[PDB]
Structure formats: C-alpha cells, structure tokens
Image (cartoon, rainbow, N blue to C red):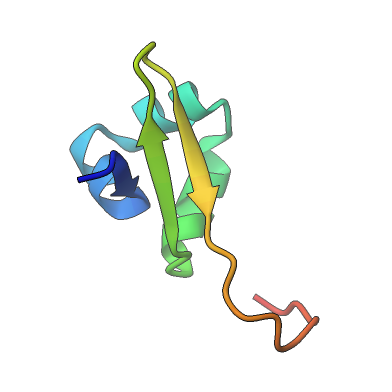
Length: 66
C-alpha cells in the first residue's frame, strides 16, 4: 500500500506539531483542515520529510465559501 496517510490519522498518530513541522506549515492551518473535514493525504519520504497531497475532484463550481 502507498504511504499516503490521512491528515486525521497522521495528526492523531504522529501529532499536529510533528506534521506541521515536517510539512513546513502552521498549526493554525492544520486545525482548520480537520475542523472542516478537508480530505487530504500526506506522503512520507525516505529522507524524513512529508508533503500533504490535495485531491482534484470534478470541476463543477468555481466559488469558495468554507
């Protein structure tokens, strides 16, 4: 299986700080990601880094609310 874990699993597993640190983001964005149930998958590298991959659903609308 691929190494694309869920933001929830990795967050509750490794933590919210350890993730935001390896990703290079702010803990503020992480909380907002799970707060709104943002579907994401962070992949673990062989060097010790991690990058959050975003899905690309079907382009139906072009608006943004929350």
